[PDB]
Amino acid sequence: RFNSSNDERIRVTSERVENMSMRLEEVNEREHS
Amino acid sequence: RFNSSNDERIRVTSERVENMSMRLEEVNEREHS
Image (tube, rainbow over all chains, first blue to last red):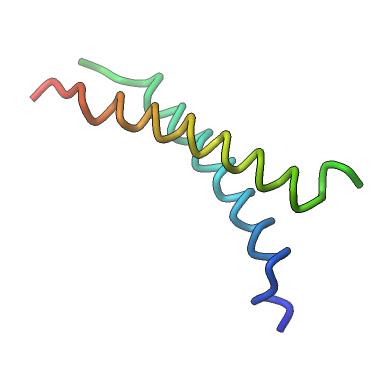
């Protein structure tokens, strides 16, 4: 019941979006060609 | 308490998703091959 609540899903989505944005900026900054 | 509210998390997630989508379209459209 705790893991399927809206607040927990929103928080986990926000954390994963932040990490994914950081990694994508890392990838884009590190192009070779 | 303000930074952990649902509205602020939704807004920040939306902004980061928009920026990430723009950067991902930039990466995908421009390829060396």
